[PDB]
Image (cartoon, rainbow over all chains, first blue to last red):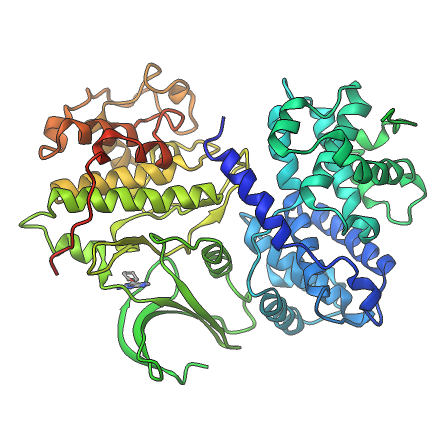
Length: 258
Length: 297
Ligand SMILES: Nc1nc(OCC2CCCCC2)c2nc[nH]c2n1
């Protein structure tokens, strides 16, 4: 119904390509790795839950961290300071009531000072040149959900769970744009919950067919199937809640017949 | 960091910080500098500056003010903007006995809608449209400025800050407590400005929230279920509201032709789902002969 929704999706299709992190930055960091990043992200999911932050704020904070790490080498010991300043900035952009800085110092377990967090806030803003308005998988997903008549709330929670699982693993998801991940997640949740398939109105809206989503969907199907074995588990724990209709208790499809 | 700027005058306080007129001592450029004192033990960069800088960098458009630089000291934050001849407020007070000619009015309005539709198509709500935040140059352009209360909205929207829009320009869905609001609130603010240009005074110079509502009810009729399904169930709607009849627009805005009255009525519909969008408003017959006169300054 919403006026501007098509213009906005077209504009988001153009900004996700400009706001995208550099795909092999991790091979050039000298001290941090993909498994450290994964742990930071899993910690930010719990911080988001403790403070009742929107999921969008989580998705933004990750976008900021990956861009910051695209051009700044960071030691493993300051990696939480990057993360904390990013969640702080994503909260200020996106939340009606952002937790205050002392709240953020505190959840660091006092690892850092307020003065460090505020100076890391200024450096992140300088490296990202204040470009905080980025497109995230959450934003694509909430637009695609406008096409699934009547809305199915389990489909919606499960697509969000899968799109949040993609934030943990830079390898392979830093390869795909948010709109394509959102596409693969929506197909896989719809499929798992009702057996229905990426809709023809989404095909006309995005230009994406089931064949162009394939590469991303094979990865995400494997991520979903192996979720139980992954070292990071706060996402699965978050999505068992009734607010998310317990979708992380559902069984993944063993195959997708593609 | 500010050594190359010379202070010319203090212009005023806007959404946040202090705004000054200043000049670049090397190039001569006259700019507007918005100063924000930060400290440190406090909160870092406030959310209004983060939004205003980030969103104005996504808004390059002839009717939107230019942000030229950001100088982020340890102590203070300066936003450096192009300087225009003046704001629409001093111009409206810099026409109150004579009145801004109609062609100028229509030109400014057509421009403010092209600016606003650009904002909305880039998912930005302004949320503080009023004459002091609109800047005109000496060639006939007008621009949206002061994005300190702006925000990026989502598709579909969620709940946003309730304390938004300066009270005279504030739409009835915020005044009545609707959980959600979206692009329609900016359009309501522009219909209030269009009418103020034409008749020479604020349309709804409410003092308080209840005063602002009852001023909109007396001119436009107390909304009921025929014009706005669900108004009678809104959070702050009261069945004991007085029931006023709607006024003819030949009395609300006498100088307007009927193309003007119809577009002003489409911008002030009560139901945000019936209020005209900025983009649909650009196709209105009122603008069929729009031209671009030069203000008299
Ligand atoms: N001429 C002018 N005035 C401004 O601010 C108006 C005042 C009005 C009252 C509130 C503070 C700002 C500007 N901002 C950017 N360019 C500007 N140019």
